[PDB]
Image (tube, one colour):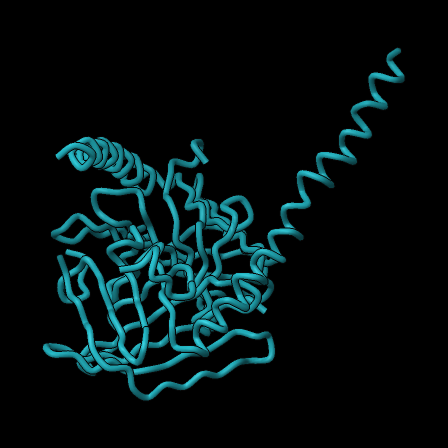
Length: 166
Length: 149
Protein backbone atom coordinates (compact mmCIF):
# COMPACT_ATOMS: atom_id res chain seq x y z
CA UNK A 1 0.00 0.00 0.00
CA UNK A 2 0.84 3.69 -0.13
CA UNK A 3 0.45 3.60 3.69
CA UNK A 4 3.09 0.87 4.18
CA UNK A 5 5.37 2.58 1.63
CA UNK A 6 5.35 5.78 3.75
CA UNK A 7 5.60 3.89 7.08
CA UNK A 8 8.83 2.36 5.76
CA UNK A 9 10.32 5.82 5.21
CA UNK A 10 9.23 7.40 8.50
CA UNK A 11 10.79 4.48 10.40
CA UNK A 12 13.86 4.90 8.17
CA UNK A 13 14.05 8.54 9.33
CA UNK A 14 14.10 7.17 12.90
CA UNK A 15 16.96 4.82 11.92
CA UNK A 16 19.21 6.94 9.66
CA UNK A 17 19.16 9.79 12.20
CA UNK A 18 19.77 7.39 15.11
CA UNK A 19 22.08 4.51 14.12
CA UNK A 20 24.11 6.26 11.38
CA UNK A 21 24.23 9.37 13.59
CA UNK A 22 25.40 7.33 16.60
CA UNK A 23 28.92 7.97 15.25
CA UNK A 24 28.81 11.23 17.25
CA UNK A 25 28.34 9.76 20.74
CA UNK A 26 30.62 6.80 19.98
CA UNK A 27 33.17 9.13 18.34
CA UNK A 28 33.03 11.18 21.57
CA UNK A 29 34.02 8.06 23.55
CA UNK A 30 36.76 7.38 20.98
CA UNK A 31 37.95 10.97 21.41
CA UNK A 32 37.80 10.39 25.17
CA UNK A 33 40.06 7.31 24.77
CA UNK A 34 42.56 9.33 22.71
CA UNK A 35 42.37 12.12 25.32
CA UNK A 36 43.41 9.91 28.28
CA UNK A 37 46.20 8.43 26.12
CA UNK A 38 47.39 11.98 25.32
CA UNK A 39 47.22 13.04 29.01
CA UNK A 40 49.24 9.95 30.03
CA UNK A 41 51.70 10.53 27.18
CA UNK A 42 52.27 14.10 28.41
CA UNK A 43 52.59 13.01 32.07
CA UNK A 44 55.16 10.33 31.22
CA UNK A 45 57.04 12.70 28.85
CA UNK A 46 56.77 10.25 25.96
CA UNK A 47 54.73 11.76 23.13
CA UNK A 48 54.58 13.07 19.59
CA UNK A 49 52.35 15.65 17.94
CA UNK A 50 51.64 14.46 14.40
CA UNK A 51 51.05 17.65 12.40
CA UNK A 52 48.06 17.86 10.09
CA UNK A 53 48.67 21.53 9.25
CA UNK A 54 51.19 24.29 9.90
CA UNK A 55 50.48 28.03 10.36
CA UNK A 56 53.25 30.61 9.84
CA UNK A 57 53.58 34.12 11.33
CA UNK A 58 52.65 35.63 7.96
CA UNK A 59 49.24 33.93 8.26
CA UNK A 60 49.95 31.20 5.69
CA UNK A 61 48.55 27.77 6.48
CA UNK A 62 49.44 24.57 4.65
CA UNK A 63 48.07 21.05 5.10
CA UNK A 64 50.91 18.69 5.69
CA UNK A 65 52.19 15.13 6.17
CA UNK A 66 52.93 14.15 9.79
CA UNK A 67 55.93 12.03 8.74
CA UNK A 68 57.99 15.16 8.03
CA UNK A 69 56.32 17.64 10.42
CA UNK A 70 56.23 16.63 14.07
CA UNK A 71 57.06 17.60 17.64
CA UNK A 72 58.44 14.82 19.85
CA UNK A 73 59.49 14.44 23.50
CA UNK A 74 60.92 11.09 24.67
CA UNK A 75 63.25 10.08 27.56
CA UNK A 76 64.18 13.67 28.51
CA UNK A 77 65.03 14.39 24.85
CA UNK A 78 62.98 16.40 22.36
CA UNK A 79 62.68 16.85 18.59
CA UNK A 80 61.17 19.68 16.55
CA UNK A 81 61.04 18.63 12.89
CA UNK A 82 59.58 20.72 10.06
CA UNK A 83 60.01 20.85 6.27
CA UNK A 84 60.49 24.63 6.24
CA UNK A 85 63.76 26.42 6.60
CA UNK A 86 63.61 29.27 9.08
CA UNK A 87 59.98 28.58 9.99
CA UNK A 88 59.00 30.42 6.80
CA UNK A 89 56.84 28.81 4.08
CA UNK A 90 58.69 30.29 1.07
CA UNK A 91 64.40 20.07 4.09
CA UNK A 92 63.96 22.59 6.90
CA UNK A 93 65.20 22.41 10.49
CA UNK A 94 65.76 19.73 13.12
CA UNK A 95 65.77 21.21 16.61
CA UNK A 96 66.96 18.20 18.64
CA UNK A 97 68.18 18.24 22.25
CA UNK A 98 67.42 18.33 25.98
CA UNK A 99 63.94 19.10 27.34
CA UNK A 100 63.85 21.55 30.27
CA UNK A 101 61.36 23.78 32.13
CA UNK A 102 58.36 21.45 31.85
CA UNK A 103 55.04 22.70 33.23
CA UNK A 104 51.62 21.06 32.81
CA UNK A 105 48.42 22.94 33.65
CA UNK A 106 44.74 22.13 33.19
CA UNK A 107 41.72 24.44 32.97
CA UNK A 108 38.19 23.73 34.26
CA UNK A 109 37.21 22.05 30.96
CA UNK A 110 40.18 19.68 30.93
CA UNK A 111 42.13 21.61 28.27
CA UNK A 112 45.83 21.02 28.96
CA UNK A 113 48.58 23.62 28.69
CA UNK A 114 51.97 21.94 28.34
CA UNK A 115 55.02 24.23 28.08
CA UNK A 116 58.77 23.45 27.76
CA UNK A 117 62.15 24.46 26.30
CA UNK A 118 64.48 22.64 23.90
CA UNK A 119 68.25 23.14 24.07
CA UNK A 120 69.73 22.43 20.64
CA UNK A 121 73.10 22.66 18.91
CA UNK A 122 72.43 25.43 16.37
CA UNK A 123 69.08 26.79 17.56
CA UNK A 124 67.03 26.76 20.78
CA UNK A 125 63.24 26.99 21.26
CA UNK A 126 60.36 27.33 23.67
CA UNK A 127 57.36 25.16 22.88
CA UNK A 128 53.73 25.69 23.87
CA UNK A 129 51.17 22.90 23.47
CA UNK A 130 47.44 23.33 24.01
CA UNK A 131 45.52 20.02 24.09
CA UNK A 132 41.74 20.23 23.57
CA UNK A 133 39.86 18.50 26.42
CA UNK A 134 38.07 15.24 25.58
CA UNK A 135 40.17 14.87 22.38
CA UNK A 136 43.77 14.26 21.26
CA UNK A 137 43.60 17.34 19.04
CA UNK A 138 46.39 19.73 19.91
CA UNK A 139 48.16 22.89 18.79
CA UNK A 140 51.94 23.38 19.20
CA UNK A 141 53.43 26.89 18.98
CA UNK A 142 57.22 27.13 18.52
CA UNK A 143 59.35 30.19 19.39
CA UNK A 144 62.96 29.82 18.09
CA UNK A 145 65.89 31.79 19.60
CA UNK A 146 63.59 34.19 21.54
CA UNK A 147 62.65 35.85 18.21
CA UNK A 148 58.88 35.48 18.69
CA UNK A 149 56.17 32.90 17.96
CA UNK A 150 56.89 31.88 14.39
CA UNK A 151 55.37 28.45 13.69
CA UNK A 152 52.28 26.59 14.87
CA UNK A 153 51.57 22.88 14.19
CA UNK A 154 47.98 21.65 14.48
CA UNK A 155 47.40 17.93 14.71
CA UNK A 156 47.05 14.84 16.87
CA UNK A 157 48.87 14.20 20.16
CA UNK A 158 49.72 10.47 20.52
CA UNK A 159 51.89 8.33 22.82
CA UNK A 160 55.37 7.77 21.44
CA UNK A 161 55.47 4.42 19.73
CA UNK A 162 58.74 2.76 18.75
CA UNK A 163 56.79 1.26 15.91
CA UNK A 164 55.18 4.13 14.07
CA UNK A 165 57.87 6.62 14.96
CA UNK A 166 61.44 7.29 14.06
CA UNK B 1 63.03 3.19 -7.29
CA UNK B 2 60.18 0.66 -7.32
CA UNK B 3 57.52 2.08 -4.97
CA UNK B 4 59.06 5.54 -4.46
CA UNK B 5 58.86 6.69 -8.10
CA UNK B 6 55.16 6.11 -8.82
CA UNK B 7 54.36 7.99 -5.59
CA UNK B 8 56.39 10.98 -6.87
CA UNK B 9 54.27 11.05 -10.05
CA UNK B 10 50.99 11.04 -8.08
CA UNK B 11 52.39 13.96 -6.05
CA UNK B 12 52.86 15.95 -9.29
CA UNK B 13 49.29 15.20 -10.40
CA UNK B 14 48.08 16.61 -7.08
CA UNK B 15 50.44 19.58 -7.55
CA UNK B 16 48.69 20.26 -10.88
CA UNK B 17 45.18 20.00 -9.35
CA UNK B 18 46.36 22.41 -6.61
CA UNK B 19 47.44 24.97 -9.22
CA UNK B 20 44.06 24.71 -11.02
CA UNK B 21 42.25 25.16 -7.70
CA UNK B 22 44.42 28.25 -7.00
CA UNK B 23 43.27 30.07 -10.17
CA UNK B 24 39.66 29.18 -9.26
CA UNK B 25 40.26 30.57 -5.74
CA UNK B 26 41.83 33.81 -7.08
CA UNK B 27 38.93 34.42 -9.49
CA UNK B 28 36.39 33.66 -6.73
CA UNK B 29 37.98 36.23 -4.38
CA UNK B 30 38.19 38.81 -7.22
CA UNK B 31 34.50 38.29 -8.15
CA UNK B 32 33.40 38.56 -4.51
CA UNK B 33 31.84 35.11 -4.75
CA UNK B 34 33.53 32.43 -2.64
CA UNK B 35 33.30 30.10 0.34
CA UNK B 36 35.90 28.78 2.78
CA UNK B 37 34.90 25.48 4.30
CA UNK B 38 36.69 25.11 7.65
CA UNK B 39 38.57 21.90 8.35
CA UNK B 40 39.74 23.24 11.71
CA UNK B 41 39.15 26.20 13.99
CA UNK B 42 41.77 27.95 16.20
CA UNK B 43 40.51 29.97 19.15
CA UNK B 44 41.93 32.95 21.10
CA UNK B 45 43.14 30.77 23.98
CA UNK B 46 45.11 28.54 21.59
CA UNK B 47 42.55 25.71 21.37
CA UNK B 48 42.24 24.10 17.97
CA UNK B 49 39.42 21.78 17.04
CA UNK B 50 38.92 19.80 13.82
CA UNK B 51 35.35 20.45 12.63
CA UNK B 52 32.80 19.77 9.91
CA UNK B 53 32.96 22.13 6.92
CA UNK B 54 29.15 22.50 6.79
CA UNK B 55 28.73 24.02 10.29
CA UNK B 56 31.89 26.18 10.22
CA UNK B 57 32.45 28.42 7.19
CA UNK B 58 32.72 31.85 5.60
CA UNK B 59 31.00 32.86 2.38
CA UNK B 60 30.73 36.06 0.38
CA UNK B 61 28.34 36.45 -2.54
CA UNK B 62 26.86 39.48 -4.35
CA UNK B 63 28.02 42.08 -1.80
CA UNK B 64 26.77 40.03 1.16
CA UNK B 65 28.61 37.73 3.55
CA UNK B 66 28.14 35.21 6.32
CA UNK B 67 30.34 33.89 9.10
CA UNK B 68 28.90 30.66 10.49
CA UNK B 69 30.44 28.80 13.42
CA UNK B 70 29.21 26.12 15.85
CA UNK B 71 30.75 27.89 18.85
CA UNK B 72 28.84 30.48 20.90
CA UNK B 73 30.62 33.84 21.44
CA UNK B 74 33.53 32.54 19.29
CA UNK B 75 34.88 30.55 22.29
CA UNK B 76 35.25 26.74 22.29
CA UNK B 77 33.80 26.18 25.77
CA UNK B 78 26.43 28.80 17.44
CA UNK B 79 26.95 32.34 16.12
CA UNK B 80 25.71 33.60 12.76
CA UNK B 81 27.20 36.88 11.50
CA UNK B 82 25.46 38.06 8.34
CA UNK B 83 25.57 41.42 6.58
CA UNK B 84 26.87 43.65 3.84
CA UNK B 85 30.47 43.37 2.61
CA UNK B 86 32.57 46.58 2.62
CA UNK B 87 36.18 47.87 2.58
CA UNK B 88 37.61 45.10 0.44
CA UNK B 89 41.40 44.88 0.07
CA UNK B 90 43.02 42.22 -2.11
CA UNK B 91 46.83 42.05 -2.33
CA UNK B 92 49.37 39.52 -3.56
CA UNK B 93 52.94 38.89 -2.39
CA UNK B 94 55.97 37.97 -4.57
CA UNK B 95 55.41 34.25 -3.89
CA UNK B 96 51.79 34.57 -5.02
CA UNK B 97 50.12 34.30 -1.62
CA UNK B 98 46.87 36.30 -1.55
CA UNK B 99 45.83 38.61 1.29
CA UNK B 100 42.08 39.36 1.15
CA UNK B 101 40.50 41.61 3.81
CA UNK B 102 36.94 42.92 4.23
CA UNK B 103 34.33 43.95 6.79
CA UNK B 104 30.80 42.69 7.41
CA UNK B 105 28.15 45.13 8.59
CA UNK B 106 24.86 43.60 9.70
CA UNK B 107 21.96 44.23 12.05
CA UNK B 108 23.55 45.36 15.35
CA UNK B 109 26.57 43.16 14.50
CA UNK B 110 29.85 43.60 12.60
CA UNK B 111 33.04 41.71 11.79
CA UNK B 112 36.35 42.30 10.04
CA UNK B 113 37.83 39.33 8.20
CA UNK B 114 41.38 38.51 7.00
CA UNK B 115 42.04 35.73 4.49
CA UNK B 116 45.44 34.44 3.57
CA UNK B 117 45.39 32.14 0.56
CA UNK B 118 48.46 29.93 0.11
CA UNK B 119 49.95 30.48 -3.37
CA UNK B 120 49.79 27.57 -5.80
CA UNK B 121 46.97 26.02 -3.73
CA UNK B 122 43.40 26.55 -2.58
CA UNK B 123 44.44 26.29 1.06
CA UNK B 124 43.46 29.33 3.05
CA UNK B 125 43.28 30.73 6.55
CA UNK B 126 40.48 33.04 7.60
CA UNK B 127 40.79 35.19 10.71
CA UNK B 128 37.66 36.77 12.18
CA UNK B 129 37.41 39.80 14.45
CA UNK B 130 33.80 40.11 15.71
CA UNK B 131 32.49 43.48 16.98
CA UNK B 132 35.97 45.04 17.47
CA UNK B 133 36.64 42.62 20.35
CA UNK B 134 39.88 40.85 19.35
CA UNK B 135 38.11 37.64 20.45
CA UNK B 136 39.64 36.18 17.36
CA UNK B 137 38.76 32.92 15.63
CA UNK B 138 40.76 31.44 12.77
CA UNK B 139 39.34 28.92 10.27
CA UNK B 140 41.69 26.75 8.22
CA UNK B 141 40.44 24.92 5.15
CA UNK B 142 39.72 25.18 1.44
CA UNK B 143 38.57 28.21 -0.52
CA UNK B 144 36.20 27.42 -3.41
CA UNK B 145 33.85 29.34 -5.76
CA UNK B 146 30.52 30.09 -4.05
CA UNK B 147 28.51 27.74 -6.32
CA UNK B 148 31.02 24.89 -5.80
CA UNK B 149 30.46 24.99 -2.02
